[PDB]
Length: 258
Length: 258
Ligand SMILES: Nc1ncnc2c1ncn2[C@@H]1O[C@H](COP(=O)(O)OP(=O)(O)NP(=O)(O)O)[C@@H](O)[C@H]1O
Ligand SMILES: Nc1ncnc2c1ncn2[C@@H]1O[C@H](COP(=O)(O)OP(=O)(O)NP(=O)(O)O)[C@@H](O)[C@H]1O
Ligand SMILES: CC(C)(C)OC(=O)NCCCC[C@H](N)C(=O)O
Ligand SMILES: CC(C)(C)OC(=O)NCCCC[C@H](N)C(=O)O
Ligand SMILES: [Mg+2]
Ligand SMILES: [Mg+2]
Ligand SMILES: [Mg+2]
Ligand SMILES: [Mg+2]
Image (cartoon, rainbow over all chains, first blue to last red; front, top):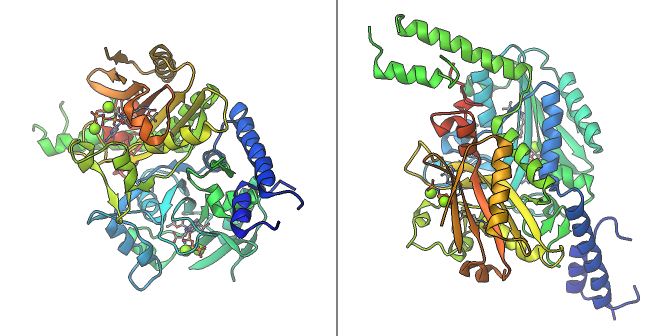
């Protein structure tokens, strides 16, 4: 008669936001299975692009076209970078770090390598310096509804002239309107949060800030970090962020357990 | 008078393959510094694309256009995958593994996640199944001239019909001729090596092989794994592979220590 909780969970795995009682679980399941196999077949026959890779390519084109230099830096970084970012056992992030060997860890954010590039590039490039990076970041997390331990961050920034809150809000606005994602910027160094309902899409700041000194900066700057899986989650109306993650269980939000 | 070894090393860092005695080190260094800053300035003014990201986009287009589905799977994987790949303390790879926590490690290759996708996709996609992935892989290494501990692999494969050595060699050939990289395929499951002089660009195999059973495959297949930094090294004539790596020290092969 009524579906068990386990049966509902199984069907939800197979349910797409798009899909719109009376028959047994086996029938409902068979219907969804056929639809999902069909979705995978269309992808294979036409586009063949992975959502996360495609979004990265689209974001890359957006920033490159706007004068930002594309950076690809190490994912495995020196543990020293963590403390240098002012992350001490006093903060939350301290215990979210995935350590590797005795001297390294998986980057929990992009900031350290971008600070290094801002400093080095200032010796060669004209003001202002505009750069960005998109790539894997890692953090141990307790939540699984809005967080992934392995996620992908976009972090863009500009240093020198034009580093105003107005310019920062303008970039964020053109960016999200380009992607077609609804948002609200909330605020009051100057820090702002880009929200979609109760979900944080990004954290942005208008420097300078005291931390800059440790990385040898000394110029004004603006920047923002966005989670690509959160952007995909909102854009594709995925109930659980796992549908937008690097995974062996979902492909473009479609269950691979068919 | 004569340049010291340390001075020559400094100048080599600043030397580009392109560049073509009498004056002091300071003069030679100043000349190279100005040229390198100019190279960075042109990149910033025009293209703005990172070599490794651009190569990945170019390789992605090549395989997607040829009917291969783009995969983005986890970089942080279960340690169990390593043993399941038949990697025991008897092999070299066993000690090259970067372990994370007690149950995970950084993927040293793409094969495990691709085996999983081949098995799952066979329940939904028409024969033959063609997929590929490009992404970070990690291995502890002793060499630094041809190896990086953090590198990027391309692994494409096809399972089902058409999985012949001839088709495999044909894909490799069209691929490298598309990129403009000279090579030689050497061989005799069936295993082949794609070489550029004494440098291994890729290892490819024509299945089936005994290992397949552990991942639930049971169909013929062909595949090959390429190192993107090695491809860049050959294409741009970089003497040391570090110029092609994710790094804070080189950008598109140009030293960032100016
Ligand atoms: N664990 C995660 N999984 C997915 N996305 C994340 C994760 N952590 C951070 N992000 C994304 O990266 C952006 C910038 O990182 P950060 O400002 O450090 O997030 P946070 O402050 O840790 N956010 P939160 O944990 O939701 O309160 C966030 O706004 C998210 O879009
Ligand atoms: N440490 C590394 N650094 C850069 N590229 C690598 C590295 N290891 C493997 N590759 C690339 O990935 C391809 C496939 O990996 P694999 O066949 O496992 O290499 P291998 O057999 O370990 N090669 P090698 O170490 O040079 O004898 C290699 O042909 C290289 O192009
Ligand atoms: C300039 C840089 C890269 C150091 O920072 C920024 O560009 N923007 C700040 C984003 C902060 C995101 C996240 N809250 C973090 O702490 O990294
Ligand atoms: C089918 C699959 C992905 C399991 O393997 C291949 O597609 N090709 C073999 C490539 C081997 C590269 C490297 N030698 C490794 O062992 O992963
Ligand atoms: Mg957090
Ligand atoms: Mg935040
Ligand atoms: Mg090796
Ligand atoms: Mg090999």
